[PDB]
Amino acid sequence: VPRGSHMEPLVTHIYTADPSAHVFDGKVYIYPSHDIDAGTPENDMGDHFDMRDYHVLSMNSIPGEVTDHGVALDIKDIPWAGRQLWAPDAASKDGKYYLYFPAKDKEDIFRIGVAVSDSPAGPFKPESEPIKGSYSIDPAVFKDDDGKYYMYFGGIWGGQLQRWTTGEYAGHDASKTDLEQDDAPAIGPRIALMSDDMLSFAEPVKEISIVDEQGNPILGGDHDRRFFEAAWMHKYNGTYYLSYSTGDTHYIVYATGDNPYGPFTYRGVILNPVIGWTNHHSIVEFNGKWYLFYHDSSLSGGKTHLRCIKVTELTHNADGTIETISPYIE
Ligand SMILES: O[C@@H]1[C@@H](O)[C@@H](O)CO[C@H]1O
Ligand SMILES: O[C@@H]1[C@@H](O)[C@@H](O)CO[C@H]1O
Ligand SMILES: [Ca+2]
Ligand code: NA
View 1 (cartoon, protein in one colour):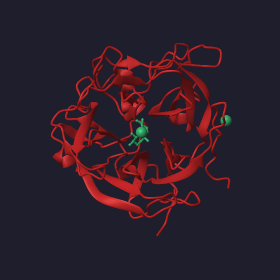
View 2 (cartoon, protein in one colour):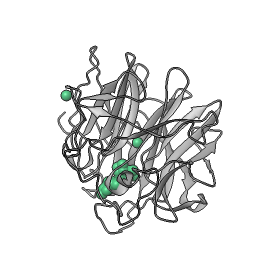
View 3 (tube, rainbow, N blue to C red):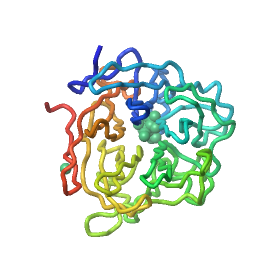
View 4 (spheres, protein in one colour):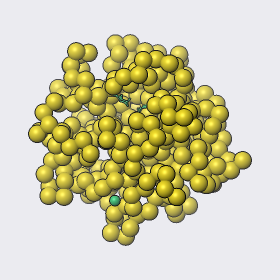
């Protein structure tokens, strides 16, 4: 039956999270995490998220019937992976489709890998090693209008971004949160231009600067505004929109800039807090309307690690500002 009419769960037969929505072949393809009831210890390192595979979803219309294409990738077939298949994304180039996914390697260090298919629905063959120079979590691979592709990535706390300041992993006894200097600039998300073949980075990884309306860096103590995880990039009216989750304050927020690398100026809230601790989203244009894909823990009765994806219309104003969505009002 058709789904996505009144902020209802898009699917209920499996738990889904962290939706990355794209328009490929005139359809909406969604690349979410596949939540399972692993029953592992819940803690601020995210051990309760013990996902093991990905399913690709698709819709021909919103609202519309949602197709589950089966298992697109299974952790048992990813040679380098140890555990934890977290928030993925996909990209399309020259008739090939690439699934980008964060997972811990056998040394328990998050890296980002790629898997390749001839179809947006998968299934995908994983590369035997993760992307050289990748680390941490939550990739978003953005195709700019000029044909260049960029990976945005990173997540603090359990996403380990705070352990990568030197370009090498600081170890499992390093910070469990952030820099632990609340008056220094907050940690920024990462960006790299993708190689022509989409399997590697074409440059050294850069950090993105996020600033307030005065041009001052967002500080580490500013948990309402500072980057936590779930980076996403979209463009509107020639402006670049970096949106992301603030984690412990439970917002999706956005910041605007004039190029892929920023800096980005914090503008405001995209999505207020949902049921369940995590908040993770994507923003996509389909048939001339903009949509916010997101999740909550409503279907599971509030279990942090058993989420369901939802969608609602997102409204840009002509001046580039976006109307804040509150999830349970209409
Ligand atoms: O990577 C995501 C993270 O952003 C958070 O939403 C928890 O679930 C993981 O899959
Ligand atoms: O620290 C983790 C973070 O990495 C994400 O998985 C959300 O839950 C938090 O506990
Ligand atoms: Ca994401
Ligand atoms: Na607002």
